[PDB]
Amino acid sequence: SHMGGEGFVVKVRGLPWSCSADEVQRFFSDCKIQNGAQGIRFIYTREGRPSGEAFVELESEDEVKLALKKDRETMGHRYVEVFKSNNVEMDWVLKHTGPNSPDTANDG
């Protein structure tokens, strides 16, 4: 079990290097993607090339779950992992390519 955070974004992992936002949008055809292809952002490195990962925004948390039910399916050639991403996580991993979560639970 893995969650990035409570957000209207999902995390799309296992995408081919040869795909654009069109193919990823077509993958989430059963999901209402926020702002269309502008809601989709591949995690591009300093090398100007995608990690094979993206963040897709969605209109509703229900739509996020419809994205999560397709977590397994083969896109391009490979199996795709669909996680649940927060607006905070999505923004930070696009600016700073790092799957390391801001783990802070000062509890007692």
Image (cartoon, rainbow, N blue to C red):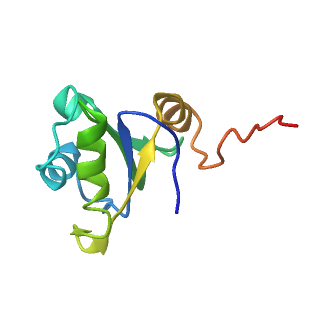
Residue 101 falls left or right of residue 2: right
**From where the camera sits, is residue 49 visible?**
no
Hey, which residue is sitting farthest right in the picture?
A: 108
The quadrant in which the C terminus is found is: top right
Q: Nearer the viewer, residue 52 or 12?
A: 12
On screen, residue 53 above or below 41: below
On screen, residue 39 above or below 83: above
Q: Nearer the viewer, residue 104 or 18?
A: 104
Q: Residue at x 26, y 51 (%)?
A: 67
Residue 24 falls left or right of residue 6: left
Hey, which residue is sitting farthest front in the picture?
A: 108
**From where the camera sits, is residue 18 visible?**
yes
Hey, which residue is sitting farthest top in the picture?
A: 35
Location of residue 100 in the rendering, given as x and y in whole percent from the top left corner? 66, 48
On screen, residue 51 above or below 47: below
Residue 47 falls left or right of residue 56: right
Figure quadrant of residue 56:
top left
Q: Residue at x 59, y 49 (%)?
A: 99
Q: Residue at x 20, y 36 (%)?
A: 33
Location of residue 26 in the rendering, given as x and y in whole percent from the top left corner? 12, 51
Location of residue 8 in the rendering, given as x and y in whole percent from the top left corner? 35, 33
